[PDB]
Image (cartoon, rainbow over all chains, first blue to last red; front, top):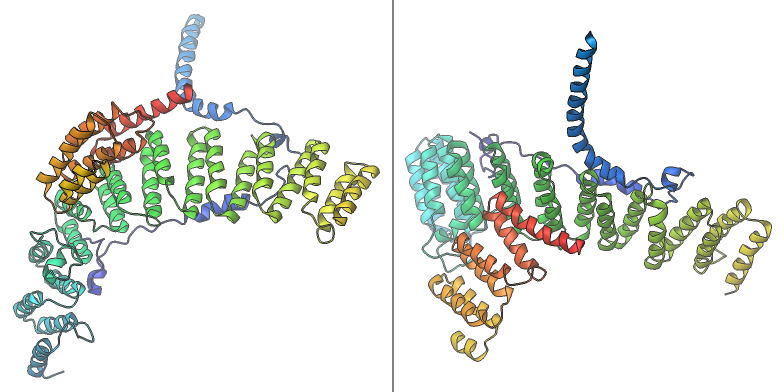
Length: 92
Length: 366
Length: 121
């Protein structure tokens, strides 16, 4: 038998209780950006990736990548079909 | 001790003499020891009769009678008479014909027990161990309708619904418990809810979580809001537009505690600093110099100007230093003038070093 | 006295106060009539979202989810979507309490569709 909500007054019954899922300190992960939160001239060296903007389409390409993965499988199939058909013809 | 008849009599005398309303030491503690003595003697039916008499008592507080009802259940658990334990708690939970308050002292103490957190939580543990899923869930439904539930009990219920793999109901349970409660409490309820959702169903149907994030942000106190802004913008970085993440970061600069806002301005600058950085942070630095206090403004002014130096915008850079010079007392802030001098030596010229000194000496006069 | 008061001061705030008073004491047969008379009286002259949010909560307590959805649709077809956000917010929470995931998303999508259409315009 398994118990999870009450806090039994018998300690012998307390032993039966299921160990409850502890949380994770989300603030600890937040600290990485809080270390990024140091006020600094973030061109700390003349790093052209900061100086020249990226393509904002990389975030768009990231969303298109998932579709491109689906497309890549179909493209690989279609390319293979042409290669199979042509190699068969070129077997002779 | 060692003289059972004397022990039995003095319990009876204690029960007769002690007024619960004047009891120094809570009266149920007598009843527990009274029942325990018979239980130690194996006289379980007499102990039950003691517990029955105990339930008839209208004690000073509901917690006294509630603790008795627990001991009624706990006795049967030790002797594995689990059906009787359920039966007792069914009678304990059993509603008055009125929709009675937990607090109305004119009502009998027995009536008030129906709301009690301890009794319902115990009965819930009984049903989950012994009985069917739907009957167990019906306890939680009553608890929610009666507004008894703590967020921990919701989290227990949520995990229970995940073990029975009806996660849609589990999300409904989180949503109901958010709707009942108020800040700060709601913060941790959101965190557990979002964690569960993002794993299985955040992959599947992303957009509902954005709206759910938006609902979570509503009225949120700044420390918890700060966490939620970063988490939402991360999700925006993981699956949405980067441009929306920047907007959420802009909210973080606005809402949060002012000293932490200065930190949040640096996050807003630094995540920009790759892609947006040269274009966007020039806007953010100007805004920050207007908003923030003199110490943080001077730090912002220098690093904005130094960024323009590395850009080569020497005319704009010296304009920022000129505006900064209004705040930089040439006596104490010598580090500012020297780092400006290091700019005038390396980038500028000897007459531009003098130009800084024309600014320095005239400001020092003022 | 409430009946007399509401006749002297016919304001939406007073009707809600009277209706909630009966509701608290569980005289639901009386409370409903107060809501029914209110939507009759105001409905042909003025339509405040405040009454319908309250009356939805009544039928929610009654568990008449079908009646609740009728109330919200009747309000949504006539009140502009830009004022109906608090209307939508309670409705979307309502569907989050008792509606299926499919039904929840469609009402949310239609709201988002309106929002994105505003972006497009």
